Image 1 (cartoon, rainbow over the protein chains, first blue to last red):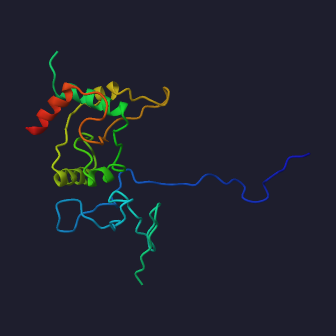
Image 2: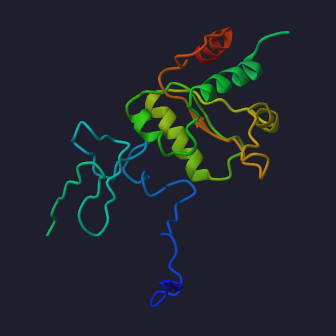
Length: 74
Length: 121
């Protein structure tokens, strides 16, 4: 046998790259007439998730990890 | 030979470490604080982020919890045995939120008593 040579495409693919904030500021914010941390993210009504769970409010859908509910805005 | 908060903090942080605890960063702390599972958090002193410190003050105002401000943290970092990663590098210990009430399920000390006395005043 020879070397199998799995190198026809993709000269060197690597692991997925994930970049994270040093301390997340997109989760809580000011400007709600409140002196406490103001809620802009949607609160999960499910018991198995909670207020520390932040379903990422992207341009579409809600992404949870355990139930993955979807809300349409139109 | 005299007990105080400056010496009770070592014992309480060590007890938390023996039982996990020490919530590094804001993540994994929002759940507990919104469920009111914590009653003593230690924050970094001389923190250079004004938004983070004001947010932490607001979060403390939410649940009415004092946060201890102690300078010269390098002694605490040496005490917690923080070099880690065998002997390569040097991570630093700057913030920790302790879960399940003030004391974990492990040992109980008069450090808890003196910290609670400082908390009530």
